[PDB]
Length: 105
Ligand SMILES: C/N=C(\NC)NC1CCN(CC(=O)NCc2ccc3[nH]c(-c4cnnn4C)nc3c2)CC1
Image (cartoon, rainbow, N blue to C red; front, side, top):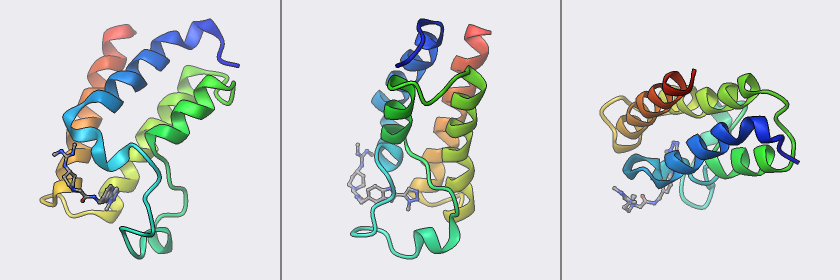
């Protein structure tokens, strides 16, 4: 399971999930609601997947955790227009994540 040295990542993820702009990213992009996603996006990522990977020992390091966070935001900018609701949310969340990351380090 998660090593205690990564508790700061667990907290950042919890705070991301609680944010106003997190709604598009809480769960895997859902084919019932969004068409054509995996056609474009080779490596989907979302906060629930991250939460499980982190809590069960799937991230050895904070760098691996951060890489998945950035994958959420990179996928969002690949799939969505910048002025779409989801596109705007991705930019908000990237800034929020980077601020919290820099605050710890
Ligand atoms: C906290 N709730 C908010 N606060 C502003 N507003 C909601 C209002 C209702 N309504 C729902 C909606 O639309 N449910 C479909 C859905 C859900 C998750 C998605 N995730 C992506 C996505 C991720 N990456 N690319 N996409 C295209 N599309 C999604 C579509 C919008 C949210």
